C-alpha cells in the first residue's frame, strides 16, 4: 500500500520509547504469511538484532536475538491475537526490563532485554505485510 | 522492482509447459528471506495447491501440495543452488511424471505429480523477492 516494504528506518530506543506499526497481511492465514520486526544495532541489514519478532500468521510467533552474527535462545509462542484477513495495530513498548508487544491494544508477548535498547540504531519491518503507519516515539529524556 | 509481488497470474499447464521466473531476494541470506511459488487450482488464493515450492534462502527448500484445504506429505531438501545477494533464474518444467526445477540452468529439485497439471488455473509468486520476469510457455498442444 503506502509505506514501502521491506521498511527500514534509522531509530533510537530507550525506556519509554514506543514503536507503532499498523499494517495488513498480504495473504489469508491458510497461506501462512509472515511478519518480521527486527531492532538492529546498525543500519546494515546483516547487523546484529537486539529484538527479533517474527509472526507466522495463524501458527506461531518466534522471538530471539542475533549476537555477533549468531542466533541465540529462541522463544516461541502460540498466542495468536492477529485476526485472519484483518488490519492489525502493533505496539512495541520499551520497558526497563523487557519489550512488551501489544496487538490491537492487547498485551500479547514480552521479551526480556538481552542487549541494552540503547544499542538499537535501525528498525526493519518486512515479509508478507502491507504497511500504513510506522512510528517511533521520541518524547522522553 | 518491476512486477508487483505478490504476483498472481491465471495459467494453464500441461506436459511441455515451462514457468520461467527471474528475480532477486529482498535480503541477505543471513536474514533468511523466503521465496514461494504456488500452482493453484483456482484463482482464489485459498484454493488448493498442486505444486507448492518454498525456498528458505540459504537454509532449505520445502515442496508439498494442499488438497481439499489440507497440507499433504512434505518433501524437504537442503540443496541450495541460490547464491547470496544474487539474481536467480527459476525454471519449472512440466514433465509427464513430475515437475523439474532448474535454478540458474542447473537441475535442482523434482516433485512427482500428485494432481494432474491440467488442474492448475493460477500461479502465485510471493514472499521476500523482487520479480523481473515471469512467463508461462504456451507452445504445445
Image (cartoon, coloured by chain):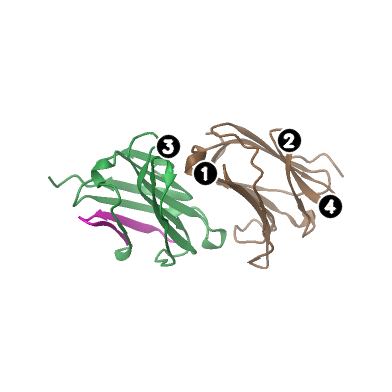
Chain colours: A green, B brown
Query: Any mark on residue A46, and which?
Result: 3
Name the spot of residue B139 as percent of width and height, x first: 82, 39
**Residue B63 appears in the figure:** yes
Query: Any mark on residue B33, and which?
Result: 1
Name the spot of residue B22 as percent of width and height, x first: 63, 35
Residue contact at pointers 3 and 2, CB within 8 angstroms: no
Chain under disc 2: B
Nearer to me, A127 or A69: A69
Marks 3 and 2 on same chain: no
Residue contact at pointers 2 and 4, CB within 8 angstroms: no
**At x 26% / y 57%, what residue is drawn?**
A98
Residue under pointer 2: B106
- How far apart are the alpha carbons under marks 3 and 1? 12 Å
What is the magenta range? A85-102
Secondary-structure class at tag 3: loop
Residue under pointer 4: B97
Amino acid at each position: 500500500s503506502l509505506l514501502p516494504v521491506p521498511y527500514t528506518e534509522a531509530a533510537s530506543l530507550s525506556t519509554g520509547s514506543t514503536v507503532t506499526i499498523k499494517g495488513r497481511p498480504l495473504a489469508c492465514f491458510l497461506n501462512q504469511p509472515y511478519l518480521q520486526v527486527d531492532f538492529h544495532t546498525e543500519m546494515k541489514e546483516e547487523s546484529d538484532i537486539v529484538f527479533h519478532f517474527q509472526v507466522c500468521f495463524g501458527r506461531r510467533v518466534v522471538m530471539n536475538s542475533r549476537e555477533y552474527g549468531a542466533w541465540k535462545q529462541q522463544v516461541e509462542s502460540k498466542n495468536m491475537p492477529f485476526q485472519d484477513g484483518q488490519e492489525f495495530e502493533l505496539s512495541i513498548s520499551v520497558l526497563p526490563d523487557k519489550y512488551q508487544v501489544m496487538v490491537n491494544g492487547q498485551s500479547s508477548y514480552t521479551f526480556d532485554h538481552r542487549i541494552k535498547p540503547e544499542a538499537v540504531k535501525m528498525v526493519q519491518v518486512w515479509r508478507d505485510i502491507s504497511l500504513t503507519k510506522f512510528n517511533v516515539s521520541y518524547l522522553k529524556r
